Image: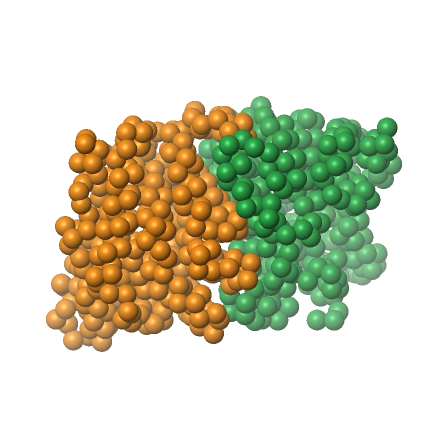
Chain colours: A orange, B green
Amino acid sequence: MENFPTEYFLNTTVRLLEYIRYRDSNYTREERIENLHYAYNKAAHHFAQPRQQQLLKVDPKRLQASLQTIVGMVVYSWAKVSKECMADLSIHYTYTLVLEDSKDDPYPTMVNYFDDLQAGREQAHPWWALVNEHFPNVLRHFGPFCSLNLIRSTLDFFEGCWIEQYNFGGFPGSHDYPQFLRRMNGLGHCVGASLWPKEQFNERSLFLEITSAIAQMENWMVWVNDLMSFYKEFDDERDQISLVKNYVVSDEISLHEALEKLTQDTLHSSKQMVAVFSDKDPQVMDTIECFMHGYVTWHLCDRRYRLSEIYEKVKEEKTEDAQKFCKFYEQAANVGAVSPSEWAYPPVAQLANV
Amino acid sequence: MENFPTEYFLNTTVRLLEYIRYRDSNYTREERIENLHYAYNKAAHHFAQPRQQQLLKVDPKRLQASLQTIVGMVVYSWAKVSKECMADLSIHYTYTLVLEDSKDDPYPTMVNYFDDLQAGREQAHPWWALVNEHFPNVLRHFGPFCSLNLIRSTLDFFEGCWIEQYNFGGFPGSHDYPQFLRRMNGLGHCVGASLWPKEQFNERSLFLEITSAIAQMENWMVWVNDLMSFYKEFDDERDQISLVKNYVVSDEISLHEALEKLTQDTLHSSKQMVAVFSDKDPQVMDTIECFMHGYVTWHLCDRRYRLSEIYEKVKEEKTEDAQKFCKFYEQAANVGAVSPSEWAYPPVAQLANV
């Protein structure tokens, strides 16, 4: 298909928000600004240090833009955790996002990975050097079990980027490949487990709840991100591999059938999220619910996804979906539309030179 | 579900072996005995050392039986790798199997996992202490990429056993839980990656086929093991959680529907295995095929799965399936039925006292 499935897309999005019970919360705009700036400020100072500036090969502007998108994602989705926790997670998820910019073959730097790890010697790959050095600031917020999940998921992600460098959508007929890759780079267990700071939750008392949340949130989070991203990726001849495009190549089905598959998985996952946790520990359901809502709000407000375009184009249609959509959208903007000048300053590069 | 779906099990099993093209190979009985003894001898001496005897808390008889099952699994499935590789892998997979015996909460021994890892200090949990100390003997056989996969999968497996201690089949309605747990403790990427020793394969030249093999083989081997195991588990109130039983609890379907799901996944996986690799690099297809056949042969011959029982009971039925089954079975026994006295000696405990 060449024309974007605007109608089909709107319907799915509306069903999605309704399933997760998208609705206003007590998390105010002023509170978001307060959190956005705190998280951004600590992270910016971190990436501005000489060592970080040295080992992390990234274009300054790309770094600035990456840091800002991640800070917004964390502050909006991990609504219930402390300012420090939001800050430390912002730094970690900015490291992960930035690794996708590397085109350098990991092979030479991974030949002695285990031996250096076991012996406690700094890793040859600079990214690992920075990420493992900083990890304790993230792990200090969690119990041993959740920490193990963050560590595994980040290791998986590193392998994920390695594979991504081959721009391989899978062999025709390799049905297990698409999701195999999406899980590898989705950071599902990192996200799912970072929602439970030991300061607010008891890892041993809620072990079953948490484990279940990690398992379910893993797929909800990656599928929602894929769906919300479908619009910006539609015309991007630069983005050649994605869950949807890989479904097409590996399963040998049409882009529309691929999008349908994603839609069914996303809705089903949303439905089961609510069915399973609504009657469980209220604190757990709150974190889960606020994450889903924040995650959606972030996608709707961040320019990167350009959903503002879908809005503009259908804010005058009397369709049922088009209207339900614009309402949800306006709701997001209301609390999420914030000018970067209100929190993202000064730029990282500025702090770096000083 | 009070009676074994024997007829269904026979049909599925036959279809399984036909799909993967089960047939005789040049791997002779005498060659297996030669490999069985070599692998067992090196591993037995390893586990008999004082340090290993000390930190590894396992009942001697259980250790002996676990070592013998694993050596068989490796020698029969990793048919194309060297004797040393078979031995070192037998040691590693015996460590993983034995971890399932632990009833000790991992929590206290994982509180400082990352900091000790980062600093190069011996891990507090004795299993990690032994496994990481021994790991290089396994990793030396592979390139950096495959090594990364073995490391991740083993780390996942450790989390898997942690979760297994709660004997939790998942919340009703938690559809993503069953497979989440099966992947966690399936060692899928460990198995899939350990099929490519750098001595026989070039990790960079075959990156795509290996990555694809890891992705597809992960599900094939866990599902086949579950199916092959359905028998010995059909009436074991001890093995309360399993992929099938978790499908029942989490998806709220009948045991028969669960078993059907597993059957469809197993056959479809087998079908896609052959379709994707048959026309690829012949050495790659050979390793994959021999692994599938060896893995099946091992399940058919190892007493643990008691498939010999299914045999006796239907070797005189003139059903099409029952006959195709007994033929395949006899084929396995022909080259796989080997008395332990021919290779598994002396017992680990004997070597430990000396």
Residue B116 in picture, x, y percent from top left: 53, 36
Q: Quadrant of residue B98?
A: top right
In the rendered image, the quadrant that contains the N terminus of chain A is bottom left
**Image spot of residue A270 (x, y percent):** 40, 66
Viewer-closest of B86 and B66? B66
In percent of the image, x 44 and y 28: which residue is there?
A123
Q: Residue at x 63, y 64 (%)?
A: B245
Which quadrant of the view contains residue A124?
top left
Residue closer to the observer: B140 or A203: A203
- Would you place residue B83 above or below residue A27 in this image? above
Residue under the image location 25 percent in, 41 percent down: A44
> Where B312 falls versus B91 (above or below)?
below
Q: Is residue B35 above or below residue A313?
A: above
Whether residue B71 is visible here, answered yes or no, is: no
Q: Residue at x 24, y 65 (%)?
A: A28
- Residue B220: x %, y % from top left: 58, 48
